[PDB]
Picture 1 (cartoon, helix red, strand yellow):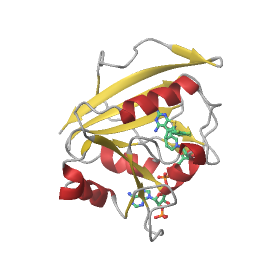
Picture 2 (cartoon, protein in one colour):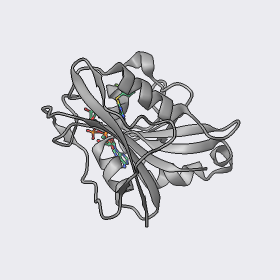
Picture 3 (cartoon, protein in one colour):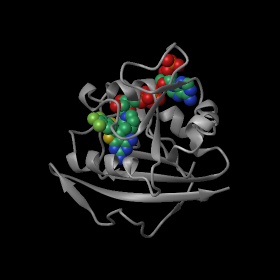
Length: 186
Ligand SMILES: NC(=O)C1=CN([C@@H]2O[C@H](COP(=O)(O)OP(=O)(O)OC[C@H]3O[C@@H](n4cnc5c(N)ncnc54)[C@H](OP(=O)(O)O)[C@@H]3O)[C@@H](O)[C@H]2O)C=CC1
Ligand SMILES: *[C][C@@]1(*)=C(*)(*)(*)(S[C@]2(*)=[C][C]=C(F)C(F)=C2(*)(*)F*)[S@@](*)(*)C2(*)(*)(*)=C1(*)(*)[C@](*)([N])=N(*)C(*)(*)([N]*)=[N@@]2(*)*
């Protein structure tokens, strides 16, 4: 198993969700970027694992579930089996990560991507180790009910560039946004 990474899109006021959807109208090229970065392996014959919470799973349009070409694992302590379409179910972040180190998965998984929501991100971000955050900055305020945890800039360094990631400002439907990558190692 290779890298651990978080990926999120976040408004200026730290917003990630509202009423079970995103705070902003759909940005196709943002979703396209998410799909590309999560799906692309850097190895041959291995797949990336995506780890998400239960509400994140059900916020994905059913036609896009499971996220194709990735191993989809959902976190929940209430569910007793993976949701229709999902692959694995785990009861904690330690267990999903322990689970990747099984003979079954260990030589099948390249990257592991945590794709939301707030509690999964907070635990990973505050756990010692090598972790990168792929953060799309949505360059305005949007009314939100679910937020991204604080990024401690003393530990996470914004990288000045990264392969396969545009640095420049983008715009779709009158909303400007920008792709960033952060890295810690502690
Ligand atoms: N802008 C973006 O990049 C993103 C946006 N979103 C949006 O954000 C909001 C969804 O986020 P949020 O409410 O934070 O929900 P989550 O996706 O984190 O789901 C929360 C549920 O997941 C289960 N859960 C979460 N963490 C764990 C864990 N570590 N171990 C076991 N179970 C866990 C619990 O379910 P149970 O109670 O069954 O134990 C909890 O009630 C939605 O609006 C969504 O559309 C989601 C991802 C990214
Ligand atoms: C979690 C998420 C988004 S929600 C979402 C993802 C995939 C999909 F096919 C959908 F239909 C959908 F609504 S969009 C997004 C993210 C994350 N975690 N990161 C980024 N950059 N973008």
